[PDB]
Image (tube, rainbow over all chains, first blue to last red):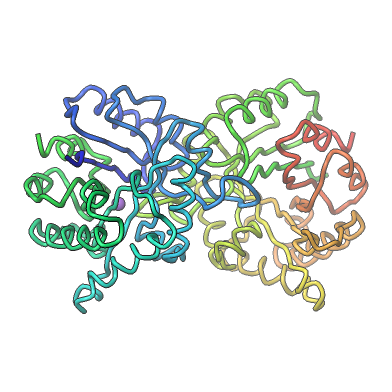
Length: 247
Length: 247
Ligand code: NA
């Protein structure tokens, strides 16, 4: 069975004190043995975050990295420096980077191949805009973004896909569980045609976009929804309730 | 007179072991009483670097930051998070960001205004390419880049300017101290016309080309060269010789 996966994207938020609060809560509150939790703080706090974790269910991820490990790339993060301080994952292709930071499908693909090759897992984000959805192109869009990665990446063992409707980000407007389920099923079937049935059956496809403590349990029986990429709620006590939503 | 300023841009290079050797070496080194040294490691190592610093003349800086302090900006660094960990500076407008990551002139200006308003110093990078130099565009380029910042910020008390002869990178040209002095003098004179004579006479203008332990001394008597923004030599023992180059 696909292990339930809950990622926490802090985005540009946090401090040493607030993150110490977040990690101590995870360390001391009841969470399942049967869960894979990955908290993704700002790069400034990756080292400190890893240093605080006291549950094996919880590891730390970066929110972005470059497609080279070293060199004259002032301002970038490196998967090697992520590993050096003990983190194990990176988010690649978040809509905020695709939209505001010029990261096209191929850049995301090249970064994904590179990260995986350096032994870092990838939380790969995909998702359609409200105009694209209204146009009926949700599947065409996520297939396109996935196709770019499929071009470069043959082995998805250490990839987790985060499907995030762009209009669902920061607006409080979550996809319905039925809709996310139908979409995840479609995505899984498309990936089966490329990666094969077994790989598609093992790949976690997460839902992201206004996921929170109240609505996480509404997704509990959606078979193709394997977890969440949590945004704002990952900074809050209810992140624990999301983690336990399939308890 | 203007205080000698030496910044060390690590770029995408470093590990916790490098950081320890580099900072402990600075801690016990004999350097001038009044030099101002800023080491700028990957964001991943900002926290750890500040924790190891004991030299009063040494502070820690980031290599880039966004133009807001918090929010839904996955993958970015924040000046408030830089401050939280005890760092004090940020490099903005490095040629590697202007080129590879499409950071436009106003983007740099908006970041500069924002960082200074948050109480973080700015190492403001400017510089023209080989193509621009060969077209006689050197001052048009730097004045454009500086004008964009001046549109947003006129109090440059907490700014140092780093001139990068991008035209000397890999091109088979070398920028000489004489070249540095001439361009710096022109830059200072332009900025006097915008900021006033007193501000311009206090502003540090750093040579941000290839400087090392061997050649840093050849800039020692150039009146308008007030220090360095050093690249690869930041990670090496000779970073100390650069700091001591005007003894
Ligand atoms: Na997210």
